[PDB]
Image: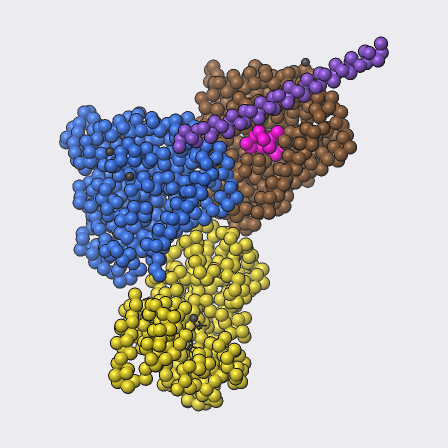
Chain colours: A yellow, B purple, C blue, D brown
Amino acid sequence: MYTFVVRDENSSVYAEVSRLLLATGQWKRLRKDNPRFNLMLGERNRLPFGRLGHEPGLVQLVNYYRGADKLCRKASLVKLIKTSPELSESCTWFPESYVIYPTDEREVFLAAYNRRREGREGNVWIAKSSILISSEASELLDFIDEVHVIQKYLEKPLLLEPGHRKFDIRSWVLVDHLYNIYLYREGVLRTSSEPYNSANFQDKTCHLTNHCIQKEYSKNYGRYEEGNEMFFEEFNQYLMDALNTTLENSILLQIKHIIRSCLMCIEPAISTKHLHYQSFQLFGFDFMVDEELKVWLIEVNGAPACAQKLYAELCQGIVDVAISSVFPLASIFIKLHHHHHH
Amino acid sequence: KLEAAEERRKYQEAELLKHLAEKREHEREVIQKAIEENNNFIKMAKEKLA
Amino acid sequence: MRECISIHVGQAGVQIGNACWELYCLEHGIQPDGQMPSDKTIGGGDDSFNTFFSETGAGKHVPRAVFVDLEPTVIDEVRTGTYRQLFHPEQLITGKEDAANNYARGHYTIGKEIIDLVLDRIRKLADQCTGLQGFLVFHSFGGGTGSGFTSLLMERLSVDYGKKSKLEFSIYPAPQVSTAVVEPYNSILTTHTTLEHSDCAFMVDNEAIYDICRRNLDIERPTYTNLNRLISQIVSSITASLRFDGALNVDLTEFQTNLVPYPRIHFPLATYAPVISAEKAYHEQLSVAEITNACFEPANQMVKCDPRHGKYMACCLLYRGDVVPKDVNAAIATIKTKRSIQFVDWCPTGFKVGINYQPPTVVPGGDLAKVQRAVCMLSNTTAIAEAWARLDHKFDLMYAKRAFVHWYVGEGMEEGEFSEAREDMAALEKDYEEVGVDS
Amino acid sequence: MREIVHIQAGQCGNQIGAKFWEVISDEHGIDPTGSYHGDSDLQLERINVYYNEAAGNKYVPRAILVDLEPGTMDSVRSGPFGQIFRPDNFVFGQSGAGNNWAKGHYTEGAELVDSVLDVVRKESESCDCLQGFQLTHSLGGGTGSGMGTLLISKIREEYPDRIMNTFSVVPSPKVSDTVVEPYNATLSVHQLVENTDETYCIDNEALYDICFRTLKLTTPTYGDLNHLVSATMSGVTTCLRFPGQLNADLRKLAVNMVPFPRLHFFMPGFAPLTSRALTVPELTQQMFDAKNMMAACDPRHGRYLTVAAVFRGRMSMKEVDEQMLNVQNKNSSYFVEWIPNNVKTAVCDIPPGLKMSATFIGNSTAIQELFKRISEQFTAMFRRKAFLHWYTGEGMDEMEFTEAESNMNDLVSEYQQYQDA
Ligand SMILES: Nc1nc2c(ncn2[C@@H]2O[C@H](COP(=O)(O)OP(=O)(O)OP(=O)(O)O)[C@@H](O)[C@H]2O)c(=O)[nH]1
Ligand SMILES: Nc1ncnc2c1ncn2[C@@H]1O[C@H](COP(=O)(O)OP(=O)(O)CP(=O)(O)O)[C@@H](O)[C@H]1O
Ligand SMILES: Nc1nc2c(ncn2[C@@H]2O[C@H](COP(=O)(O)OP(=O)(O)O)[C@@H](O)[C@H]2O)c(=O)[nH]1
Ligand SMILES: [Ca+2]
Ligand SMILES: [Ca+2]
Ligand SMILES: [Ca+2]
Ligand SMILES: [Cl-]
Ligand SMILES: [Mg+2]
Ligand SMILES: [Mg+2]
Ligand SMILES: [Mg+2]
């Protein structure tokens, strides 16, 4: 009997992983503060990593990588990309971003904001934190004061027909205890149900593609697809019919490159390869696609939820590759790897 | 701080030896009660017969 | 030349001191009878080895050492063992009954009756010193004597030798070899009372040494003899700068200056490589780059914790054997580009390096293979606070129910001393977080 | 920490006491004349804990034999190791105690107790550094129960900084001499709760059930019961008697095993059970099995506050550590989470006619079942004041029985409090 504890009651992914472990009959749930566990399904904040791997006779595994927050907080991601040689200031798949406090990057942000004014270039930006869209600098900075990042807003998104409507792509990625990077083969498009309007940023329902914002404010919620959720089989059909390409070629090569670049960058800092306890973590990567079919990373989520119909398959995937790999009982993933010589 | 500790140990000890002293007092009263009841039985049998 | 006095307290302190002095004799060519043929100045001198050894007219080299235990059985093994002639009887102090794994019994009840005798025997060693630097104190956190007697002794040494450095070598408790459920109580009580009296403390987690012995020496079930021979190698690495000619960590004061910029944050992490099995019939000898890279592996640390997730305030590399600065500097450059080494903003990002050309000595018939080069890294990292967090959590679990507290109160300690000691550890955990974590 | 003084009181105390000295004399290579004829230095290293050295390298048990009647001590003096005891350490009256706690504690026992303390003082005075006392007795009779607990109170008065340890045989209707056993046991438990540091609860219910169910003895005798007791007593004193790290003296055992002063009643266990070759997995599973416990309590009905495990024989220390970790990890819910690492393990190289054995000492909240069972038998009689005249005849009042019952019900509540926490 392998043993596990549950320290985050509000996680839908790990409530389902918990139910699956119990139904194998080879896993026993302990009280949350019992130290004699094989597996911690940990809390989101102040997880006590310092108390892991000091139980003699127990191999201990946690479902979070200590230090992964560098990737999964807006301010940290911007700093990590600029300052890591392997991502660099000249990184082509991350929007031009600046950290802004109410250290700071105000006067470097204004300098670049003037080059667009100067050259008559499209000069819309987005302020956000762990939300406002304007082409006027001093209105963004006023709002912040009233820790944030100002990020170039993507003025030319790809638009789904019918509906002339914006979207983002969620990819789920599992990093196992050996630092294999597994991309779940099912992603999801979180769509707008409103047509896109480049002359009205005040109205934020046709600009922001979150599942909560469209469910409340948008008066077309569910008109095109169940939820505001288009899955890969349909989006691939759409790209073949309308644009004469595939999801694999036009978008997924770039997504896989970006996931591998982000996670290979922090590997020396978070790897548990030679450590007294071991880690895995499920990440949610959020992408925008522009009208040239160029892919942009928006953010990395350290504690994502899943689309309703993919819970079953993904959670079984987590027990198969993350947990049973370490604790064997008595593929839905693409393994991201590339060994090019130069 | 060392003398203060020693005085708390001496206090707890004097408290114990007082409690054990009440126990010896009670033991002395049980056996005197046993004697007094045997003597009172003999006495009262002697008087009833007379 | 400036003398150091070593003080070994309780079973762990005494058995580790046995292993250290055995090793020092082998390193300096001192025989079990105290004779040192290579020493041409008979009856005295101010050589570097005289920091740790005094000399009689008859050519006997005598450790500047006191051994204290509250029961006799461990020190009786020194009195009748291989090195019995090395020590004069007045250096070896024993009581009749021990502190029964109880800080309060060591500190208050039995400490009060033996403390004046121990200070008298220490005063006798101090009186033969022309320039006493101070004290090296070896003890467990977990035992009643190691915890309670040591904290009383450290307080009295601050009073009687106010200008003297005090360095500790402290054994942090591990359940794989521990003998008491109350070791976390004893650890927090002694850390609280000692913290203001110690300049620099090297913690050794018995769990880390145990695992190094299992993993790297292939010992199925390590004994204290196995653990102590490894601990003595690391202690010898640390004290070598006091016992040999050199220009780094040459006095006790220099340990504080080089490793401890903030007085309360005085617990450097030791990391040692390489540890190689003597039974291993084929061994490929490790380069300067390999042993230096091994200093950044948690598996080689004296305390298991993750320095990638804290900040450095100081780093010393102490090399023994065939090492030149060129190879050290190339090793460091390679490591900087590959590892997460983050210093605090107010400290230079840098390494102080010491090289002693004499390779590490091993005890004949021991578990350690003879190697051509070895290194001990001493780093002051905030990551060592993980070990405080573990101990504080175990303390909190038991103290919430007052489990075993009546044994401490029964020795004349107040319950208040528990919550005061614990509050001092909360403030220590917070000090490490302020220095270590960003916002 | 060195010398232990052993006291054995009444029929039960002296019968199990004599078997204890036979068994440990054989382990230490001491023959019935007190001469050492053993083959190992391990046998003599801590011999002084239990034995005095006399003229001509003779070893004499630090043992005092007490009874209010001579019969059982005459049988000891004639028994195999009878000539090894110091003759002046036999202290006996002629009256007997009639299975009456009041006679042992207040009337007959009070007459004899001063001459027992004279012998305790003589043994105590020649100790380099006395650790404390162990008493063997039953709680169901009069001398062991009533005079035994009187002695404990007087020893505490004269040696208040020393440890007091008992081997206390709890009565059972299945192995019963009189109906008043529950009265004698309740009055005794009230004394033990206040005046011992550590009590081994040896339940005649459990010993009978082991002899009947496990060892297939159709008709268990006191001899069969005492074979289990002497093997357990050898097991639980191994760490006091042989070189070792863990629980090596009475005060260190108490500090490891007793988190609250009143909860000092231990459930001993032994494996294998005996009237050919046991693996470390099998020792470990059997030593933790309800059927190997010497107190008739289901450990799955409570939680372990603390456990000491002692393995004896030539075996793998790695396999002992792995198996002991396996039991805790697989049954984690039965070990209180608020005493971390509450299971300690010792290994001694000298086995007891076995190649290997394991002794278990548990401080379990399930021990409340033993006290509740005695409490129910006490109340059934006490509600009708049945058989009280035997006690009021010796000067006792009903109120003393009401106080003993309340204190034992309080002890039950306290075990229940830590079981729910
Ligand atoms: N590394 C190592 N640890 C030891 C040694 N001896 C004991 N320990 C550890 O020290 C702690 C117990 O403290 P001891 O030093 O035995 O106790 P003491 O200081 O003698 O105190 P009392 O016996 O209580 O008077 C536990 O954590 C043991 O594992 C030893 O030789 N080496
Ligand atoms: N630079 C940019 N250009 C265009 N649209 C952008 C953008 N940055 C964000 N968005 C819009 O905002 C959405 C994401 O906002 P953001 O990711 O900052 O919030 P959030 O963290 O609440 C989402 P999640 O629930 O996935 O964590 C995208 O779906 C997109 O519609
Ligand atoms: N296990 C065991 N129990 C005994 C023995 N002798 C008596 N008993 C039990 O002890 C109790 C009677 O007390 P006993 O020691 O005979 O009376 P005492 O001489 O007045 O102390 C009853 O519970 C009996 O079941 C014995 O040799 N072994
Ligand atoms: Ca000289
Ligand atoms: Ca000072
Ligand atoms: Ca008489
Ligand atoms: Cl001074
Ligand atoms: Mg987000
Ligand atoms: Mg000791
Ligand atoms: Mg009888």
For residue A257, side relative to residue D81 (left or right): left
Residue at 32 percent of width and 39 percent of height: C197
Q: Position of residue C69 (x, y in %)?
A: 37, 31
Residue at 49 percent of width and 58 percent of height: A39
Q: Tell me if residue C132 is in the magenta stretch.
A: no
For residue A137, side relative to residue D220 (left or right): left
For residue C27, side relative to residue D325 (left or right): left
Quadrant of the rendering where the N terminus of chain D is positioned: top left
Tell me where residue D129 sits by quadrant: top left
Residue at 35 percent of width and 51 percent of height: C431
Q: Is residue C423 visible?
A: yes
Q: Position of residue C426 (x, y in %)?
A: 40, 48
Q: Which residues are magenta?
A: D191-204
Q: Tell me if residue D195 is in the magenta stretch.
A: yes
Residue at 49 percent of width and 83 percent of height: A193
**Above-or-below relation of D41 to A20:** above
Q: Farthest top residue?
A: B50
Out of C156 and D77, give the one closest to the viewer. C156
For residue D241, side relative to residue C119 (left or right): right
Out of D387 and D165, give the one closest to the viewer. D387
**Above-or-below relation of D5 to C312:** above
Q: Quadrant of ligand 8?
A: bottom left
Q: Position of residue D326 (x, y in %)?
A: 52, 49
Q: Position of residue C261 (x, y in %)?
A: 27, 49
Tell me where residue D265 sits by quadrant: top right
Out of D176 and D102, give the one closest to the viewer. D102
Q: Is residue D356 visible?
A: no
Tell me where residue C294 sits by quadrant: bottom left
